[PDB]
Amino acid sequence: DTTICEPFGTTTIQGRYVVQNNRWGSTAPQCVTATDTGFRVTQADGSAPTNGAPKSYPSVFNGCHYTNCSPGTDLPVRLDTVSAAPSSISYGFVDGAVYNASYDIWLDPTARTDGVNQTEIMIWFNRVGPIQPIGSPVGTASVGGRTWEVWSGGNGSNDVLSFVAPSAISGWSFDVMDFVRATVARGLAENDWYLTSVQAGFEPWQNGAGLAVNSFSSTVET
Amino acid sequence: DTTICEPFGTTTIQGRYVVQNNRWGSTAPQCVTATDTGFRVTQADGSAPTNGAPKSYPSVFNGCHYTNCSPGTDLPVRLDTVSAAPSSISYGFVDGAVYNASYDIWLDPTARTDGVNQTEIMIWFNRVGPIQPIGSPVGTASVGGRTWEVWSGGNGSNDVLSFVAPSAISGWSFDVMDFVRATVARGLAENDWYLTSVQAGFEPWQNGAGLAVNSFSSTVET
Image (cartoon, rainbow over all chains, first blue to last red; front, side, top):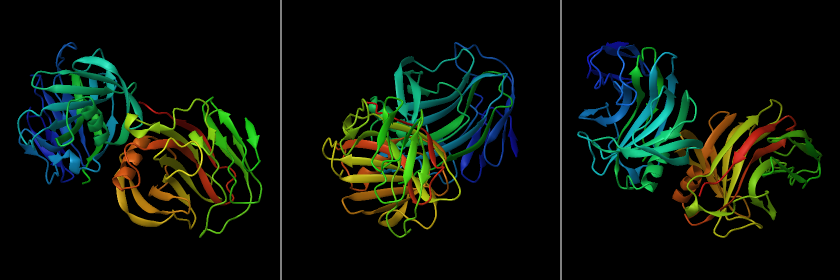
């Protein structure tokens, strides 16, 4: 295991994914501990107002996030060359934090390895507390066999389309291209765009220690 | 509950799906009992050689199968009008039968309510015994977040593309359009074809009593 408390510290797991503390929105201590198959939040002090941004987005990812590219990633990859982009996750939840458990999937018109990507897809697997996605609710959508409430809006530097689960999903295996297709269908990407990263972790607003990504996988079939 | 032993007997469940005994390939008694959410095989005598056709395909379906259309089905529906075709299943398996647990998804160029449909997609959720799909193995494919061995061939009256699970899947929720897209990608359908039925059940070669479809759902989002 590797513990990271530096706000912008990262490490690699399984020779392929990057674990990032990513404590961009808080000044109180936060640490993650990378394990063989994922990571756990081992400290997450402080509270951010629930009507604003979260404290951070501790997470694990395949792909390129602001110059940081996981070892041997196939991303960024052009979407029309992808037959499938399967991803799986096992989340560990705890009862005394205000947070969401979410994937952040980034798409762009260029093979972006750095800088803000054009469109962000968010998949909320769990939500505890009076928090809500960026933008406003636009109705439901069936993606991957499950029903989601969809939100769309612009978070500042870019567009964000969120798919929110009705109740907690602690583990799932799915094709990231299903959500990409739903995004293309809403006019926020095109088929010849690039998938630049697939990330999963938590956005905590209050506490967060104990939350974990027990396992994660993300590949691309071309 | 409703018991059906007539070879070609059917009934409806939940006001929307058809349960069919469909004992087309055996002369020995076979009965199914339709329940509130699915059906069970309650008798399935006889054995068919494992290098040939199975005895039958007792199953539940949404759509139109040889003139028999489930109550209020949205099928046949044109594929380019479908945003999603979610389906879910809970299978009950037993240890002394030779069989597969499979979905049969039929596609055609016309809004077919009767007669042989052009292309059949088979999804094998479980396989017990020395049986194999129609045709020959053509490699693997990731569909819906899971990995499948794919087979293709022509069964007599039409083309068949099968996706076989590596080990038993007792319950899953998925989008039938993911498999349709993989079929379109292999040249066995086109995007403006029709989805004419989504069926799930078992193909038994030896015994089969005790096998069940505990629950099934199949809808189309347009």
